[PDB]
Every structure is written in structure tokens, then in C-alpha cells.
Length: 144
Ligand SMILES: [Ca+2]
Ligand SMILES: [Ca+2]
Ligand SMILES: [Ca+2]
Ligand SMILES: [Ca+2]
Figure 1: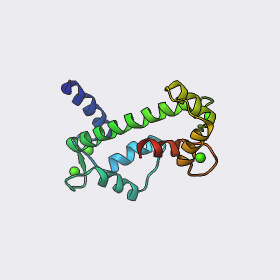
Figure 2 (figure 1 turned 180 degrees about the vertical axis):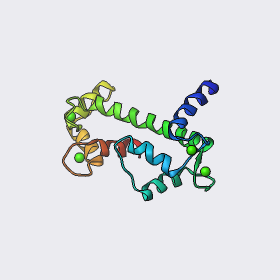
Figure 3 (figure 1 turned 60 degrees about the vertical axis):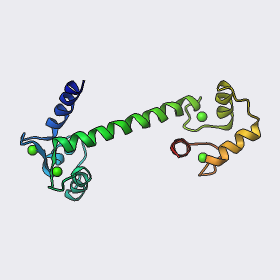
Figure 4 (figure 1 turned 90 degrees about the vertical axis):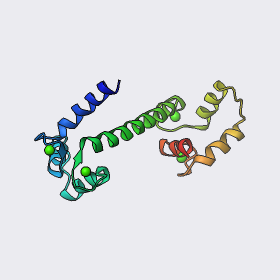
């Protein structure tokens, strides 16, 4: 249902294209951000456009917005999947996965590990050496 898909993307684009000329400029991007409680500098506004402007003409057109929007979507889907799985491991939602927590989910996965085996797993991902795995350390282990 691309047709319906493009429609939703067109809708998003129009929010930024304040004057409707078919392009988004630094100033238009600027008014959108400011309405969000963010007052970026012209320098920051230029870096944002630079990242998305494939033909280097200085503005973003629909096709350029579409391709970036897409790639961004895919990525937002990744993050929320990993964040979901983090919540399942962090049985007490304290923000960190302990040895005991990791060992209990592992048994549920069909792997009966000893405390020493779980401790080794934690150690491998434990960057701040606090004996637990935080989200940052979890994504590192996940992705990498
Ligand atoms: Ca415009
Ligand atoms: Ca462009
Ligand atoms: Ca926890
Ligand atoms: Ca840690």
C-alpha cells in the first residue's frame, strides 16, 4: 500500500514545508524545532540539512525526506525491540540486569546455568564494572 504510505509521508513533509514550495529550508526546519521547545542555532540547523541533502543543493525535497524518513523508521523499530527485551530481563525495573535476573530468564529459555557461568556472562558485558548490565552495555552486547 505504497500509495497510502506515500500519503502519510506527504502529510509529514507538509508540516515542515511552511510555504509549500516543495522544499524544506534551514529557516523552515528552524520554526518546526522551535515549536518543539528546541531553539537550535543556524550552525546546528545546517548540520541537520547536510545529513539529509543528497544532491547538495542546500534544501530538502520530498524524495530526500522520504528516503531519510524510511531509514529512520527502520532504526526506531530496532531500538524499541531491544528496549522491549531489556524490560523482560530487568525483572525489577531498577534499570539494571543482575546475575540473578539473567539466570532466571535463562532457565526460562531452557538453559540452566550455574552462578559462575552467569557471572562470566555479566563480566563480558560489564563496562563500568558495577557487576550489572545497564541498557548501554546491553545494546553493546545485543548489536555487537
Ligand atoms: Ca518550503
Ligand atoms: Ca537537496
Ligand atoms: Ca534489575
Ligand atoms: Ca555494568
